Figure 1: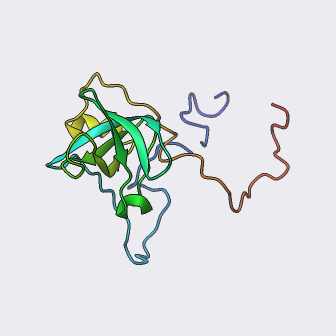
Figure 2: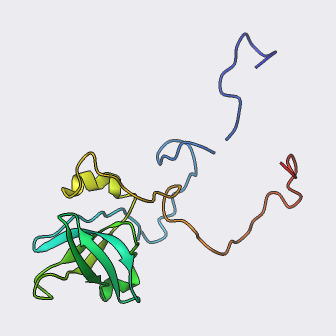
Figure 3: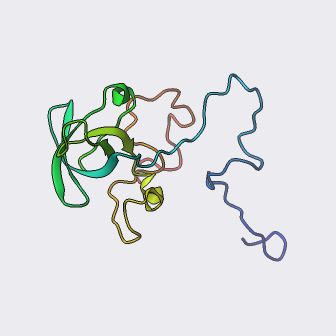
Length: 14
Length: 143
């Protein structure tokens, strides 16, 4: 969410 | 673990260990009418009343006894003319999941209300195997 590449998407494996 | 599909990039398989699985929903049959259970009796029979407003004791099927699931609040199909009318023997069991299809069963309207749903497929499922991945719980202990 913070610090990666502008704005990531879907970073929660469930 | 979300999105319950089939084809894509999950599970992965291809052994074909003797195919013996496939969905097969059944609808009301000619001569037989659908019904709704209200109360349960001993075991070989159950208390139910047809959506039309007819209370009758539907006896559990023999052959279906191996795969017949009856409930006090579920849809079912019972054959008529076998008990000289009035009574009807459950020919097959209309599951709750199927209930969504019941609109398709041509029995219940779009405003009909279905009871029980369960988190996909039947519930309860006593006894468990493996039970790996955890042991010490981790992350949460008291919640």
